[PDB]
Length: 45
Length: 50
Image (cartoon, rainbow over all chains, first blue to last red; front, side):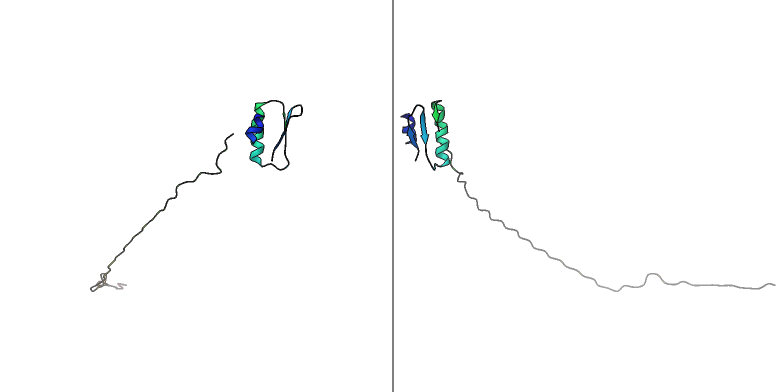
């Protein structure tokens, strides 16, 4: 939920580990995502 | 999560340069120029005793 709010083309799902998926994302969005990666160790990009 | 700007807007500076120069000259060459080295007197002697 926190990452969904902060990010809010990227799609967020729960699965077993929180998963982020997107087809054509700008490099800034990818950088923001990998920065938010430090919030939770079990994230799948 | 903050990102930097692509670049920074700098102040623009206008330079105005002036280079001024004046030259003046005078040349004169006047009078009479004479010879200062001339031939001098000569003397010669010759004899046959025998």
